[PDB]
Amino acid sequence: EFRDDACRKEIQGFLDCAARAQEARKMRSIQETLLPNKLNKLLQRFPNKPYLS
Amino acid sequence: STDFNDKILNEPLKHSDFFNVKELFSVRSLFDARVHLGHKAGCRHRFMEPYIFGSRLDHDIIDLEQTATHLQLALNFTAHMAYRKGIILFISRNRQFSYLIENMARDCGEYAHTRYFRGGMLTNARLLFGPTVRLPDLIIFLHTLNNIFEPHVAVRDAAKMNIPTVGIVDTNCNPCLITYPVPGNDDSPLAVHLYCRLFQTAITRAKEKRQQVEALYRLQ
Ligand SMILES: [Mg+2]
Image (cartoon, rainbow over all chains, first blue to last red; front, side, top):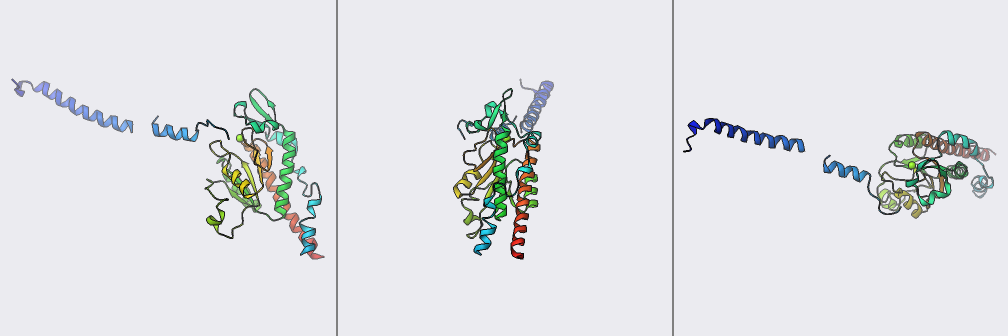
């Protein structure tokens, strides 16, 4: 009947898991930040030459 | 003025090797410096085939006999220009040798441009530098390719502006527009050092001989 008093354990688990989800979002963002930018820099350094020179 | 010019400028033009550049090198010295090593056969350029001796295990070997002849011609031209007091500009985008080439230019009293060649340095020179600027009388390419394996735009611009170009052309280079190509290895430090030393020595010899001839003429 939605009485949290006797659902305390499950509610605490849910809250802790949500906090862990936010923490995981933060850590994943910082970890994401080879990167496409660096790889494009490398490819620019060594470009494909489909023509003559 | 007439006799001075006749005996100073035109006198050396009557001799096959007035500055004696052939003594500055031998095929053995070029070999020891590894001037004969080119790129893989896949990187080869169609216009560099006449100068390639062969292919040793998919690695091109530059004919050092042709290199010796071409280097003789290029060094003689450079010596004559330095004697005539023309501006000699050394161009190279090989960052491994930028510092060395700049030092060689400073020591020999000539100029160097080893940095990012901004568009118009030669074709737009009057606007960029000033209407009375004096463009180089000779451009010496220690590496005719830029840093993306394309010909240095200075080659095309020098051809446009009618500035003769000496140039070390590897097996993957395009010697079509280089006035004096010197087929050789432009990637080995030994080869680059030999080229720098040769051009420095030739230019210094030419300048000192110019001073000596001027003194001889003016003292009489
Ligand atoms: Mg090379």
